[PDB]
Image: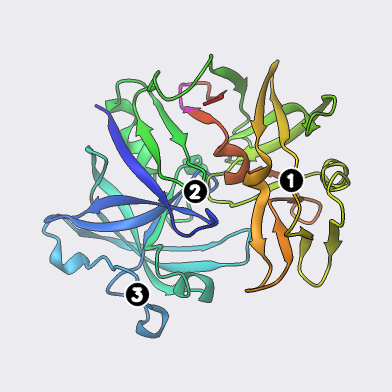
Amino acid sequence: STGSATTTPIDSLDDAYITPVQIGTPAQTLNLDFDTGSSDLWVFSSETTASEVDGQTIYTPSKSTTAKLLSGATWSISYGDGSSSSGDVYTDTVSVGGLTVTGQAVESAKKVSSSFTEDSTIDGLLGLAFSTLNTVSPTQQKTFFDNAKASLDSPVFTADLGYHAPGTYNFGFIDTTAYTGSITYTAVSTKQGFWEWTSTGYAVGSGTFKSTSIDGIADTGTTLLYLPATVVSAYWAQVSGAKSSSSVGGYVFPCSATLPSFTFGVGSARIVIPGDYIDFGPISTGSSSCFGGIQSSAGIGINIFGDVALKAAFVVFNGATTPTLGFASK
């Protein structure tokens, strides 16, 4: 089998991307944030505290003839941005772009933190990291990809995120028309549960490439590119007036600037992030200070190749017995 679904930016800055997902019988379609940095499929539901729902579409398990309570199971997750959610668990039928999994754990939110409530466009998350990170207790559950893998034509999914435009998640096949050149594959460590790999270096604009190993994760659920402070300083030093602001929470730059590109290495290959992809717009409405899309990871504990980097590439998440990542230009 295969599946193919369009993923759409939630706003004009590409802050996140939503993909429609069919849950239950008859189908209830929810727009989920596909997150290669986590491993829980959770949704706003008829169980979510009513004051914490503000415009999201909810899953109602009582209206699904295939829903079954997973007795005794609970879940609770906290994300890198400080947000969180928790609840109980059903199994139900879940389809993405024509690909169907029966018996998928659908984690029904009883509580969500304010950032989720405040984002009316995201109805939940669909995790695509390794199932060892799944938070369901006392019986850990598998991701949608893990459950589908054996049925897929090839044990892979791909992320093709757009810049200010829709893109595509494919399951089970590699669309050879969706990228230019060749795909360069690179080793993955699953030891932390992430699609963790090592970039071979970077360049700023037309500058020379610096060969240096940068361990980080491919994370579709993070908006920006988080890299070591040395690399990030070298980038912003090329933008007149750019500075790190503790009050804003990162690097800002004059909105009048033209930003340089940023290149990252994948083995001997190179992915170029155009400068415009690194502009996240005014820090507050009407400001002439703009927020940068490359930020320091020094406070995180890990480097994160988020959407800013991934949207510049066609990315293969290869879930073979030994997983690997592939990157192509497009």
Give above or below for 327 relative to 126.
above
The residue that appears at 74% across and 47% down in the rendered structure is 258
Residue 192 lies, with reference to residue 255, above or below; the image says: above
Secondary structure at numbered mark 1: loop
The image quadrant that residue 151 belongs to is top left
Specify the principal SS of the magenta part.
loop
Image coordinates of residue 217 in percent, x first then y, are 63, 39
| Above-or-below relation of 246 to 214 | below
In 3D space, how far apart are the residues under numbered discs 1 and 2 (Cα atoms)?
A: 17 Å
Q: Which residue corresponds to mark 3?
A: 55
Image coordinates of residue 98 in percent, x first then y, are: 22, 38
Whether residues under marks 3 and 2 lie with C-beta atoms below 8 angstroms apart, the answer is: no
* Highlighted range, magenta: 317-321
Give the mark toward the camera: 3 or 2: 2
**Which numbered disc, 3 or 1, marks the residue closer to the eye?**
1
Dot 3 amino acid type: Gly
Element at badge 2?
Answer: loop
Magenta stretch: residue 319 in it?
yes
Q: Whole-Å distance between the Cαs marked 3 and 1?
A: 36 Å
Circle on res. 215: none
- Residue 168 position within the rendered picture, expressed as x and y whole percent measured from the top left: 39, 38
- Please report whichever mark, 1 or 2, sits nearer to the chain's N-terminal start: 2
| Residue highlighted by disc 2 | 164
Q: Label 1, on which residue?
A: 259
Q: Position of residue 150 (x, y in %)?
A: 31, 26
Q: Mark 2: which amino acid?
A: His
Q: Quadrant of residue 83?
A: bottom right
**298 lies left or right of 285:** right
**Crowding near the residue tagged with mark 1, few <14, some 14–19, many ≥20 C-alpha atoms within 10 Å:** many
